[PDB]
Length: 288
Length: 287
Ligand SMILES: NC(=O)C1=CN([C@@H]2O[C@H](COP(=O)(O)OP(=O)(O)OC[C@H]3O[C@@H](n4cnc5c(N)ncnc54)[C@H](OP(=O)(O)O)[C@@H]3O)[C@@H](O)[C@H]2O)C=CC1
Ligand SMILES: NC(=O)C1=CN([C@@H]2O[C@H](COP(=O)(O)OP(=O)(O)OC[C@H]3O[C@@H](n4cnc5c(N)ncnc54)[C@H](OP(=O)(O)O)[C@@H]3O)[C@@H](O)[C@H]2O)C=CC1
Image (cartoon, rainbow over all chains, first blue to last red):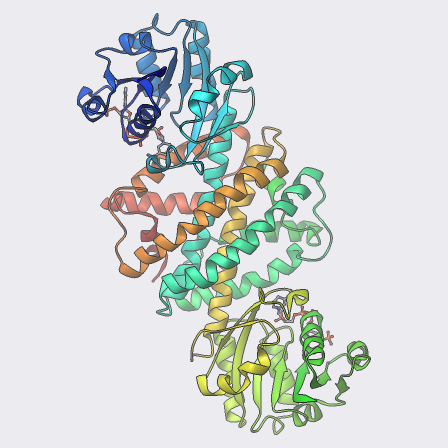
């Protein structure tokens, strides 16, 4: 292995995928896992198995941590508190913005540099260009390791505050859960009349959602300008579709629990006298 | 010089329908409760019917594009003998029940009846990306589908006259989920003073585009009643949820729009089915 050394801490599904990709691109790859047996498949394709946290940290300057949660990351760090000096830690362990900031503070106090990353991909997609990985933390630190990290996917630096990658990650997941709420309600409705989901989804729902997804750029601009529009696809107009959806759902025996919240928000805005505004107005309503 | 059509209702959508029929050479008779709305159509060749009865008499294909089912019934009931041996194509939005009720009246008055759901705004009428759902007797639809094809892409969804409306409302339900997601995502980034436009254009839209394609695999699982074991399990989703909730709380963002799916996921995990995937949620809201 002729390329710059990397150590990977955590050899679950994701850490295994990261280590595999580093090895495939010729990096000297040292691996560590709390349960040491998980290293064996990687040893078989050229990984070096570190017997301790301390020796994994010593083997490389770039130390990737991909464990379960922030508590587990802290447990790893605290096991060898002098091992991190002059190292760059890239923490790809999911958590809150606060978790990233707290971990960074510890790392900085122990002589390490620290970047947080959020992997927007499943393990199988690591190493593909479609795998987006968000990163945040000091720009100069990121600059030093971004070429090595680019083996994993498309690097997307989102700023200096170390908690920002996690915020972007969780924002994207929130978007996905809305999409899945819509899928669930739509498919329940057609399934309630014995319509197969696959044909409906492939030929009607996906094309419709694709068209409506493009509308989001205009909404985003309105959010930024704090100018929610007048007439058109107003909230007054949306509030006219809602009773049909609710009544049809009730008649088909489909619960409205997943869609009722946005309908209640729309109705609140109408009742405040702002029915002429559009959907961009809803963002400020859920903010503090 | 082409086959006659009558359009009842000259709002934004009815005007667009009449305009497209005229552009494709159909003799187009128009009627509206407020007669002034006919004047622009007269100027491009429409015949203005003085009564509902005379609009019905002018054509075999009678398109009704009004506000709601009550308004459709008001039009029909004004001239109860006018509809015999005519094909009514009702493009007025409502519930499946509304379409069935209207069809029952039409059939009792000697008419044939198709319901359609326009998944498009008026200016898109006549374009291939305008999908129009239709339901009702297949043999009736056969007789009018070539004329109707000038309006958009015909999508026949079956015999039960309420099915076009069910498909339409299902699609809208999907959209409202998408908008719930947009709202929460953008609130979160805005709470940290991140501009929405850059985030949406370069991160959220590409991500949602990729997740939208994943819906085909979920749909297959729903149909097979086989919700998977491991992978992107509900157990895995239930680990992201507390991070989203805690970060939202810290940023002062209400979780009212996403809490319901999190509660459904948690219920399924607690029933011992955490190894199943998101396709399991469809059956949970059915009953
Ligand atoms: N899988 C996925 O699709 C995605 C995962 N992620 C994130 O990547 C990270 C890793 O996920 P994934 O690999 O799939 O999860 P796995 O459950 O497969 O692996 C979790 C890893 O964390 C380790 N770990 C748990 N507790 C501790 C501890 N106290 N001290 C040290 N190590 C510990 C495990 O060690 P041991 O083997 O000894 O149990 C294992 O290496 C998580 O933050 C996850 O949210 C990000 C995007 C997608
Ligand atoms: N426009 C859109 O973006 C979309 C509309 N649709 C559906 O198409 C239909 C028409 O929409 P659109 O034209 O845009 O709406 P408008 O408000 O522009 O038009 C409503 C029409 O209904 C008529 N109407 C209202 N009440 C009655 C009544 N009691 N008797 C007779 N006619 C009546 C109005 O007549 P008058 O001029 O006298 O007021 C007008 O012609 C609705 O079902 C709508 O949901 C479907 C897809 C999207």
